[PDB]
Structures are given as C-alpha cells and as structure tokens.
Amino acid sequence: GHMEQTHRAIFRFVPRHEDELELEVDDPLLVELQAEDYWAEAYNMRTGARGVFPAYYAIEVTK
Amino acid sequence: MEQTHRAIFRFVPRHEDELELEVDDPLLVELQAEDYWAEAYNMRTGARGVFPAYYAIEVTK
C-alpha cells in the first residue's frame, strides 16, 4: 500500500548525533520501532529523513 | 549546588555525552543550549551530561 503516519512530533529536537532524526513541532512521523531504551526509530514525513529520537517527543495518532 | 529542574520522562543514553534520567530525578541544569539540549548534573546519580530539554521542568523556587 502506502506510508501511513503513526505519530506527530510535539517538541523540537535538533540532533547532536548522526543517528538522530530532526523534529519540528507538528512533524508527521512514521514510527518503525519503539526501542526498549525509550528511543523511537522513525521516518519524518515532512523531511524524508530517518533516524532516532527521544520517544516522549511524539504522540500516537491512530486514524 | 541546589536543584533547578526535575526530570519528567525516562531517558536512557545511546551516546557518550548523555545524562541518564529517571522520572522525578533532581537536576542542576548548567545550560539550556540553543539546540534544545540541556546540560546538567543529576543530583541523584552524580553524573553530568546532556539530555533533550523538554524532559525536565523547573522546580518551585
């Protein structure tokens, strides 16, 4: 099928590290993995970037 | 050295520079950096490092 948004970013996140996913508030995200260390692995549907971010920076949207 | 902040979310480092947080951890924040990372001392663990800034709230002075 198609890429479906799973989450929305609610806080700004600016990477310090090469594996991180930059977030702006309101970014639509497709979260691929919620890791046990409370990082999320995702595709940012605004930028097309992929990476990890601190998991409490996004809320689930389930249309 | 008195508490400035309280952790509100669990944060487990992936990176060398990061500060581990448990919920309710007392923090002394030295810098709120312009890239939305906080630079702090965890007053429970005695560790120093950085964490994503919205993981801590200011305490009632």
Image (spheres, coloured by chain):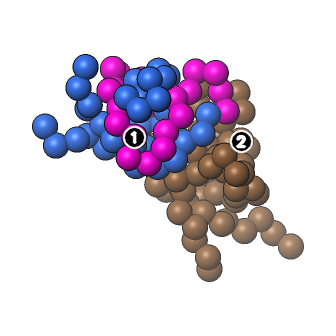
Chain colours: A brown, B blue
Residue at image x 26%, y 40%?
B58
Residue B37 located within the stretch drawn in magenta: yes
Discs 1 and 2 share one subunit: no
Q: Position of residue B61 (x, y in %)?
A: 13, 37
Foreground residue, A14 or B27? B27
Q: Write down the region rendered in magenta.
A: B14-40
B41 left or right, relative to A36: left
> Residue at point 62% right, 49% down?
A38
Q: Is residue A12 above or below residue A14?
A: below
Report in which chain the residue with disc 1 lies: B
Q: Can residue B55 be seen here?
A: yes
Quarter of the view holding residue A53? top right
Q: Is residue B55 above or below residue A56?
A: above
In the picture of the structure, the residue carrying the numbered disc 1 is B25
Chain that bears disc 2: A
Q: Position of residue B16 (x, y in %)?
A: 64, 21
**Relative side of B60 to B16, left or right:** left
Q: Is residue A54 above or below residue A17?
A: below
Q: Residue at x 44, y 48 (%)?
A: B23
Q: Residue sitting at 53 percent across and 34 percent down? A: B20
Amino acid, disc 1:
Asp
| Residue identified by numbered label 2 | A51
